[PDB]
Amino acid sequence: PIAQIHILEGHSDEQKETLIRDVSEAISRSDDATLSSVRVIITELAKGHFGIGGELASKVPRGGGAGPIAQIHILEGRSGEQKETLIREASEAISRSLDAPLKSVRIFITEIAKGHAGVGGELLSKVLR
Amino acid sequence: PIAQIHILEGHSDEQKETLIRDVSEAISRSDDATLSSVRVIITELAKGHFGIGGELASKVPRGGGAGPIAQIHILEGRSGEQKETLIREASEAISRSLDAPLKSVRIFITEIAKGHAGVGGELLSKVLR
Amino acid sequence: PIAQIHILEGHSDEQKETLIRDVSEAISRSDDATLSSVRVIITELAKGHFGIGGELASKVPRGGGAGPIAQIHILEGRSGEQKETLIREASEAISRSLDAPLKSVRIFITEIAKGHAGVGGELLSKVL
Image (cartoon, rainbow over all chains, first blue to last red; front, top):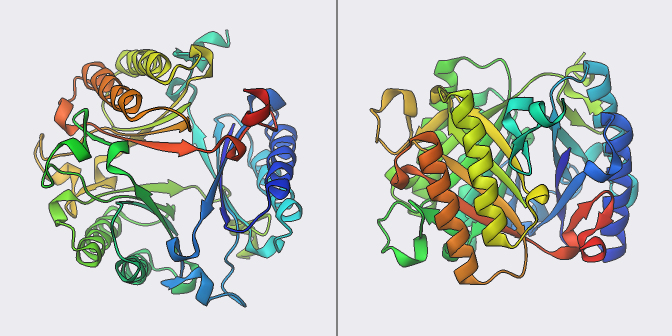
């Protein structure tokens, strides 16, 4: 699985490494994937490049929810409950790693069909066999 | 809904602020979503990192088709007609905000299935009830 | 490196397989990355979900500008010439694989700092 995590500027390198480790362990546990196959990309958001309700994030601090946004690409074949656990445990991993309020953490999942997933130039549905 | 909008370098902070405001209101009206729940991520693209027809945008004089690219994540349940309205009005908002030719603006919609979107570690479909 | 390739519906499964193989080799050679480390995600875009100039791709004739859109995440450290070659050869790989007009193919590169990329829970700046 692949997690693209947009985070706010100003986090320490130490938080980012903790974010990468904990979220990858959470995704591994929750997606039933090997740890080694989990890739994480951190993208930092300048406050002038992040909009909530049409406002810059810097202008909606108290109530707007400005927080990490994660898109997790997983292969097809997981149940609703396993994907719910993925969303919960990855969000908890993001929250404690960044000391960000859990309610500000947003995660969405995109499912990839095996015929749309390539590793080393080969379809996953064919190397699996 | 979440809009990831790739724009070229060189836009002003006010253009970026106007883009966030104008596109968020257009997305709100067309997605039947609360304004506060619309999120916009602006990503700047160096022209040496943008390929059109295999040629760098920086090596082809402007007018070559290098322009904004937006991906809009919305929840399932909107009709084809509502999605076409979303695409048209958000594209116009991008064009007028960045003073970018409309013909250069690309938008695509990715639908999130219910149970694939989380806030605070909880499914949107379950916090909803 | 990771390639997210948004393509229009209607391509055959063999075109999709050839796309994944040809682009992965194009990325591997040009990014100086091991083939096994090249990941490709195909996302199919319904023509009712693809806008050019505010008009649906389904309502504009072919060559209206609807074409593949690829985002390639690579680690920092490649030169402009290497990145231009990556863009050209990946775009050519996409065009011939999908029998899509080359000029309708859009590719952009996103650079990742070494400390912003995680593999197996460890920073790429450590695994390398």
